[PDB]
Image (cartoon, rainbow, N blue to C red; front, top):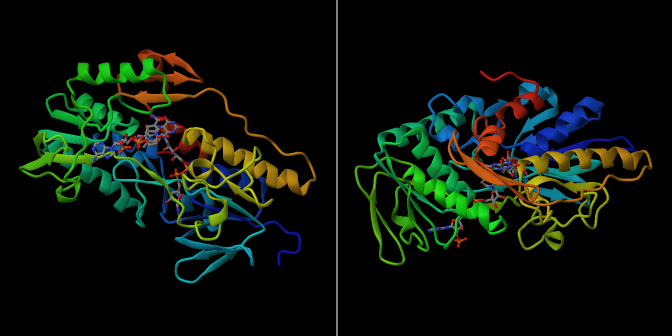
Length: 367
Ligand SMILES: Cc1cc2c(nc3c(=O)[nH]c(=O)nc-3n2C[C@H](O)[C@H](O)[C@H](O)COP(=O)(O)OP(=O)(O)OC[C@H]2O[C@@H](n3cnc4c(N)ncnc43)[C@H](O)[C@@H]2O)c(O)c1C
Ligand SMILES: NC(=O)C1=CN([C@@H]2O[C@H](COP(=O)(O)OP(=O)(O)OC[C@H]3O[C@@H](n4cnc5c(N)ncnc54)[C@H](OP(=O)(O)O)[C@@H]3O)[C@@H](O)[C@H]2O)C=CC1
């Protein structure tokens, strides 16, 4: 029993979780941030950290340095809604007056990294990836969504002498929600960089392929019988909302996508003190780091507003903002529903990939 006192538990230390923890910390509200890793991952820059020697150490930020005893490393395995408890692997339990679920998404390395690991092992995993790319003259990227087009562009921009093939199962590249003008310009930039495109083809022997590892010879096969020989295979084949921590407890509340249904105040439907933020929230908006941060501000604010019997803040989407870096010198996208060009995207995203914003939030300086 908390007897009216606040204790907020945040499950997930991604873009959403560190924003929520930073604000609760500034408000002196008791809270615990739980993450399976020992450091925040600026995963927007994970593909650049896969091609540039020495960059990976700019993409991982120690939780304990920023949050100290308000941070607990661990894997959440269930939520006990009756006794308001966050269940950790190992048996430990965390009581909460309010729960913020910020579990993000999972997917293949290198675009996502969700291993229980130390900070130096995580950085080394990306430095090893750089070494695999450097050893490999021929490289195949599988999947031409927004991650795969960025991956292929990063490789050919850093290493123009390598041979890069992107294999994609659809006719057009990147997200279907994007303006057709954006999707066509993505294709043209890749072709001008020398990336070979194999569109409307599905790689069919994924079980048989060594992944993220240089080999003298790998044969990639497609459902149409195309065969590509390569030294290296990288999967950018998509992500899944990470519902492990909460799927059982909230099964009745889950969208199809695995997200949690929520109102414009981001409380989970059926609950007044549970919030979902970021990728695991059924925003129906695109899953974006910057939206996770905005959701966190809304979530923390209505926890406080709700204790002050005040009216709640509301999340209202606008047109789609979506920026694709195409290596450090190029890119294309849209800012709230209109096309923005290559100079704009290069300056806004491609050069720095928003890395400095996470170090600022965490109040740390990059090594
Ligand atoms: C891959 C990629 C993504 C981009 C990219 N670009 C942009 C961009 O330009 N702008 C943007 O806003 N988003 C961009 N994104 C999307 C952005 O990465 C995601 O939308 C963002 O990470 C979502 O933030 P969340 O806070 O919702 O989730 P995270 O995945 O960041 O963090 C979740 C955390 O929960 C932890 N966790 C999950 N389940 C757990 C459990 N059961 N126990 C403990 N910890 C758990 C995970 O380990 C992880 O640390 C991009 O170029 C690439 C290549
Ligand atoms: N710049 C940004 O803001 C970025 C944002 N994101 C976010 O992350 C989300 C996921 O993006 P992404 O990670 O690119 O995942 P996506 O699911 O968007 O793209 C993955 C693609 O890979 C294709 N694919 C899967 N298996 C194969 C195969 N065996 N052979 C060939 N093609 C295959 C899929 O086609 P099928 O589905 O037909 O199998 C799909 O079109 C985005 O929706 C966005 O919210 C990610 C990267 C950049």
